[PDB]
Image (cartoon, rainbow, N blue to C red; front, side):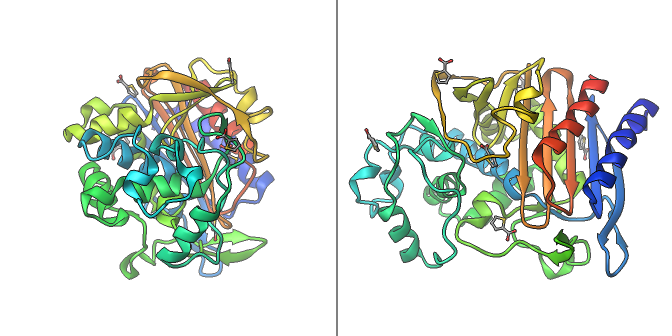
Amino acid sequence: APQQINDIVHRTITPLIEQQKIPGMAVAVIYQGKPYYFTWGYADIAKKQPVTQQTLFELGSVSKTFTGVLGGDAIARGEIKLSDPTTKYWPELTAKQWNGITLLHLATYTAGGLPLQVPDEVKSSSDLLRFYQNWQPAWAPGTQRLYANSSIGLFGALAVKPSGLSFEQAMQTRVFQPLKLNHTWINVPPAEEKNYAWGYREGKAVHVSPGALDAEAYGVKSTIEDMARWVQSNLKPLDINEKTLQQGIQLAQSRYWQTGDMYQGLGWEMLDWPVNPDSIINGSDNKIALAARPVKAITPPTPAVRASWVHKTGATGGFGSYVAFIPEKELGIVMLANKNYPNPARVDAAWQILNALQ
Ligand SMILES: O=C(O)c1cccs1
Ligand SMILES: O=C(O)c1cccs1
Ligand SMILES: O=C(O)c1cccs1
Ligand SMILES: O=C(O)c1cccs1
Ligand SMILES: O=C(O)c1cccs1
Ligand SMILES: O=C(O)c1cccs1
């Protein structure tokens, strides 16, 4: 690799791993259409398996970027519209609070205060109807952003209905296959368990538990190589041969709402480049708190802006993830770790790395 990339990465991540006590980590720097990969430590501490470029990490909420792009692809295929009422795709959702609630609202956490998690007690389709029917919004739709797996989760399940496919089958055939993401899974197959890192929470090996709408919200597992290939796809969507996917990518990085310096996409979140990293490390958008934030409608949404810092953070109980990229500079980073560690620390490291290379 270029020494500059070697040097800044090792100098940023090595202290990070020490301070946060991360068992294993994988990083990709994507620069001018080329990836550069770094690994540290252990996928499996007990079996002394090292992190490699084929190690699978749980992405957590970075999964939502796939969901965003899959939904944007369904839009480009003419199957759904973000302006459509939720009840168009789920007519059994007859409770009156759902009047005015669109697929845009679900996709961007603006439905009016959908809760962070689908409850664990929700298992069947009947349970899921019951849960959504019985939810009472705090706010009118399109007024406040509150981050929620139950919001974008439902968006993901409804977006694929007209296709005829299960979410998993739609994602595989429409996003993973076309982009050649061959080591990216919603369900890790027995053949790949050898590559699947354990997460560590309080020093215990853990994997993400099954739950309603897990695939759509936090359930994707991937390797650093496939994740770099994902960053490259989102950095240069016009290089993509499949027209509805290329368009779906652009729809996912479009700006639908503003709060402070952040713009809400479909899965992806954006700031204007150059960025002052204080809001995303120290201030209102550092993700420490679950934050109800009034939003300004971007009417109509701004098409994907090249001069953006585009990012998404994710966690499961055992894992911490981060992806950020600047299409203008043809520059991106993926950071995958098998311990959940504070988001500000993730963003601080990413910023130091990309600010130095840009
Ligand atoms: O105005 C409305 O639709 C609402 C106010 C509070 C919950 S929904
Ligand atoms: O796998 C590949 O060719 C690439 C991943 C990121 C940029 S190019
Ligand atoms: O985007 C947000 O507000 C959050 C992501 C994770 C916790 S809060
Ligand atoms: O800049 C503005 O007017 C607003 C940001 C968030 C709600 S309104
Ligand atoms: O090339 C472009 O216009 C873009 C790449 C990513 C968002 S817009
Ligand atoms: O089991 C886990 O780690 C999680 C379940 C839902 C979000 S993370």
